[PDB]
Amino acid sequence: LAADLAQAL
C-alpha cells in the first residue's frame, strides 16, 4: 500500500 500512496511524490 505504501508504494501505492507514495507515488504522489
Image (cartoon, grey):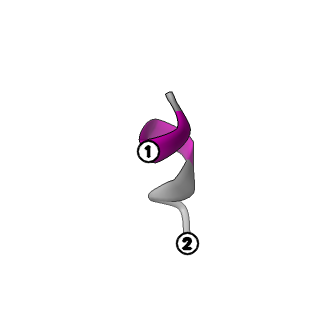
Q: Which residues are magenta?
A: 2-5
Up the image or down, 8 lies above or below 4; here it is below
Question: Residue 9's x, y, as percent?
Answer: 55, 72
Secondary structure type for disc 1: helix
Q: Is residue 3 magenta?
A: yes
Q: Is residue 9 magenta?
A: no
Query: For the view shown, which residue lies furthest in the top direction?
Result: 1
Left or right relative to 3: residue 2:
right
- Disc 1 designates what residue? 3
Q: CA distance from mark 2 to mark 1?
A: 10 Å
Q: Give amino acid for label 2.
A: Leu
Q: Give amino acid for label 1.
A: Ala
Q: Earlier in the sequence, mark 2 or mark 1?
A: 1
Left or right relative to 8: residue 3:
left
The secondary structure making up most of the magenta span is helix
Left or right relative to 9: residue 7:
left
- Disc 2 designates what residue? 9
Residue in view at x 44 percent, y 45 percent: 3
Secondary structure type for disc 2: loop
Up the image or down, 3 lies above or below 9; here it is above
Question: Residue 7's x, y, as percent?
Answer: 45, 58
Q: Nearer the viewer, mark 2 or mark 1?
A: 1
Up the image or down, 5 lies above or below 8; here it is above
Query: For the view shown, which residue lies furthest in the front direction?
Result: 2
Question: Residue 5's x, y, as percent?
Answer: 55, 44
Query: For the view shown, which residue lies furthest in the bottom direction?
Result: 9
Residue in view at x 44 percent, y 38 percent: 4
Up the image or down, 1 lies above or below 9; here it is above
Residue in view at x 54 percent, y 38 percent: 2
Foreground: 2 or 5?
A: 2
